[PDB]
Image: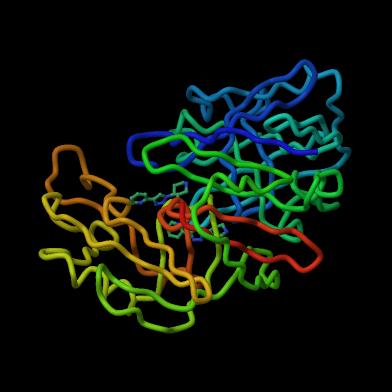
Amino acid sequence: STGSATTTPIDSLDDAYITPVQIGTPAQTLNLDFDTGSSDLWVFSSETTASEVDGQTIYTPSKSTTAKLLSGATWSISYGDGSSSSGDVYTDTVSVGGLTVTGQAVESAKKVSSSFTEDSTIDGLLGLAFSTLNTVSPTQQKTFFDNAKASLDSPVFTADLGYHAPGTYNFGFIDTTAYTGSITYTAVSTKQGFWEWTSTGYAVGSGTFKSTSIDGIADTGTTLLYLPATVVSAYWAQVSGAKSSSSVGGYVFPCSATLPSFTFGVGSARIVIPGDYIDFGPISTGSSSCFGGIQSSAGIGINIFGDVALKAAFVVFNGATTPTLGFASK
Ligand SMILES: O[C@H]1CNCC[C@@H]1n1cc(-c2ccccn2)nn1
Ligand SMILES: O[C@H]1CNCC[C@@H]1n1cc(-c2ccccn2)nn1
């Protein structure tokens, strides 16, 4: 089997991407944030505290004839932006782009934090990191990908995120028309439950490539590119007037600037992030200071190849017995 679904930026800045997902019988279609950095499939629901729902589409398990409460199971998750959510658990049928999993754990939110409430475009998350990170207790549950994997033509999914444009998540096959050149594969460590890999280095604009190992994660659920302070300083030094602003919370730059590209290494291959992908617009409405899309990972503890980086590539998440990651230009 295979599945294929279009993923769409939630706003004009590509702050996140949503992908329609069918849950239950009859189907309830929710727009979920596919997140290769976490491992819970959770949704706004008829159980979510009413004051914490503001425009999202909800899952109502009592209207799904295939929903079953998972007895005694709860979940609770926190994300690196300070957000969180928690609730109870159903199993139900979940389909993405024509690929169907029966008995998927669907984590129904009873509580969500303010950032989730304030984002009316995101009805929940679909985690695509390794199932070892799933938060359901007392019996951990499997991700959608893990449940689908044995039925897929090939045990893979691909992320093709657009810049200011739709894109695609495919399950079970590699669309050889969706990229240019070849796919370079690189080793993955699952020891932290992430799609963790080592980039071979970077370049800023037309500058010389610096060969240096950068361990980080391929994370579709994080917007920005978070890299070591030395690397980020080298990037912003090429943008006249850019500064790290403690009040704003990272590097900002004059909105009139033209940003240089940023290249990262995948083995001997190179992925070029165009400068425009690094512009996240005015820091507040009407300001002429703009937020940068490359920020220091110093306070995180891991480097994160978020959407800024991934959207410059066609990315293969290879879930074979020894997982690997593939990157191609596109
Ligand atoms: O949410 C976490 C889920 N697992 C992978 C890492 C990810 N992540 C995101 C951030 C972060 C940090 C600062 C500002 C915004 N996001 N830190 N970790
Ligand atoms: O990574 C993202 C995962 N979904 C929740 C918001 C989170 N997020 C975004 C930003 C951000 C975006 C643009 C400019 C400055 N900050 N910080 N955290």
* x, y percent for residue 76: 67, 48
Would residue 259 appear left or right of 319 to someone viewing this image? left
Question: On screen, 143 above or below 188?
Answer: above
* x, y percent for residue 236: 23, 68
Would residue 317 appear left or right of 261 to someone viewing this image? right
Of residues 22 and 204, the one nearer the viewer is: 204
Of residues 123 and 182, the one nearer the viewer is: 182
Q: Which residue is drawn at 25% across and 56% down?
A: 248
Of residues 10 and 244, the one nearer the viewer is: 10
Q: Residue at x 83, y 26 (%)?
A: 67
Q: Which residue is drawn at 70% across and 39% down?
A: 87
* x, y percent for residue 62: 79, 19
Residue 325, quarter of picture:
bottom right
Q: Give the colour scheme of this rendering.
A: rainbow
* x, y percent for residue 269: 48, 70
Specify the quadrant that holds the N terminus: top right
How many numbered marks does the figure carry? 0
Q: Which residue is drawn at 76% across and 32% down?
A: 94
Would residue 262 appear left or right of 120 to someone viewing this image? left
Residue 212, quarter of picture:
bottom left
